[PDB]
Amino acid sequence: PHRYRPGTVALREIRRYQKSTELLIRKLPFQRLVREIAQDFKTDLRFQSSAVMALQEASEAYLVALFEDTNLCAIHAKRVTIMPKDIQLARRIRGER
Amino acid sequence: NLELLESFGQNYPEEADGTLDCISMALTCTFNRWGTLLAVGCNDGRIVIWDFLTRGIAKIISAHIHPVCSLCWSRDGHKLVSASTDNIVSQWDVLSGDCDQRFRFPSPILKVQYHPRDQNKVLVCPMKSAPVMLTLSDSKHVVLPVDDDSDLNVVASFDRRGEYIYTGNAKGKILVLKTDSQDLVASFRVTTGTSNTTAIKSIEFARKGSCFLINTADRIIRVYDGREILTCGRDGEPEPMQKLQDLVNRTPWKKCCFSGDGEYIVAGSARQHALYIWEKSIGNLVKILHGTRGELLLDVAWHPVRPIIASISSGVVSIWAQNQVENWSAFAPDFKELDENVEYEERESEFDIEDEEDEEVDVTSV
């Protein structure tokens, strides 16, 4: 019958994930994603492994920066819950679209 | 044969238009005389024939076990000749597909061809030795004598009319021979570069006149006229009508053929799978084409009376014609779709004006 007040697990996971560094997305689905969208530019390529790790690091850093600027937007609108008009606002302001 | 009122600014091929996603593992391609069929060899030794007007697969004939790498049509369109690593002089029918000739003769063959008027005389180009001309009934074989015997790579063919036999070694020396008596009437070494010679890969001809092509190995396609060879005669020194190359990517070629009217030249890469089209007369590139960006090109065809081009890559045979644009006034010719304010006053016979067959044509003619 013991359950937390909602939000506590959220904040402790925030601290638990900021106190560590690792690859965060599971590696083989991301590798299959990279090969599948590299199909369209030159058929039957041959990657190395370190290039795939470099892509995973670049994409992970880009998503983390995007979500922090999204969270700034959502706190600015006197809300807490992130809605995708925040993300579209952030990529409209930053200049990528 | 087709519509005569169709020519609303006809074009020269631009689009992709859709391919034959039916049977892969294609190896070579060639059309018949009019441009109505297309034989295509498989990988295991079969024949794929595709009809054009119905856009339908005509006939599948299983020849042998060795892969089919050389094909040609007869003049009537009834005798297919072919040869492969099977070493066999073959001859096939189009209504039945019968093994009419079977003579396993060594040094496997790289190219066959009929004489363009008599289908009795057929061309045989061995693996090493000099090219051979044969008959149909008996084994009368004519090996053309070569002074070199050192390349063991000699190319030869018949031209449009079958008047002569243009021969070529892999040193770039040409020996013109008469088509029946083997008269060495003309000879020339190709003026390659500054001085140093090159090999000869293949030689093809036209459908109208005597302009033809030389496919060397120094990445330079050369265009000559056969009447200039005839005007020279022996110890000729021809300089070409037009030279062809692409030094941006320095691309050696794999296959060439002419247009139907002898006006345009297509030639294909061995590296990029990207087709180029040239003008014969004025002498420049007109259009680059593309495709699947990382495939290896094998064989390129052309359709004579209609701008259709066949490619071969990864066993897939493309067909490229305009993705043509349809409009109104074929459903209703009394109405024409304009664009802007068109004025109608030029005729003067308006405002209530009132003024004051015998051809017998056959119905079952040709």
Image: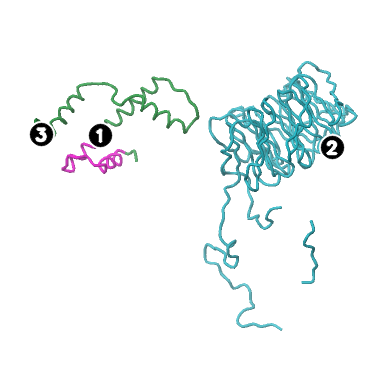
Chain colours: A green, B cyan
Q: Which residue is mark 3?
A: A5
Up/down of B321 relative to B342, above or below: above
Q: Which residues are magenta?
A: A69-94
Amino acid type for the residue under numbered disc 1: Phe
Query: Quarter of the image holding residue B119?
Result: top right
Please state the horizontal and vertical placement of residue B164, each as a whole percent of the image. 85, 33
Up/down of B175 relative to B78, above or below: above
Q: Are marks 2 and 1 in contact (CB under 8 Å)?
A: no
Is residue A83 shown in magenta? yes
Query: Quarter of the image holding residue B295?
Result: top right
Q: Chain of mark 1?
A: A
Task: Measure the C-alpha gap from mark 1 to mark 3.
Answer: 25 Å
Please state the horizontal and vertical placement of residue A52, each as a whole percent of the image. 38, 23
Task: Assign the C terminus of chain B to one quadrant of the image.
Answer: bottom right
Left or right of B278: which side holds B151?
right
Q: Are marks 3 and 2 in contact (CB under 8 Å)?
A: no
Q: Chain of mark 2?
A: B
Left or right of B307: which side holds A54?
left
Amino acid type for the residue under numbered disc 2: Asp
Q: Which residue is mark 1?
A: A67
Graded by Cα atoms within 10 Å as few (under 14), some (14 to 19) or many (20 or more), the crowding at tag 3 reads few
> Are the residues under marks 3 and 2 on the same chain?
no
Q: Which residue is mark 2?
A: B118
Q: Chain of mark 3?
A: A
Amino acid type for the residue under numbered disc 3: Arg
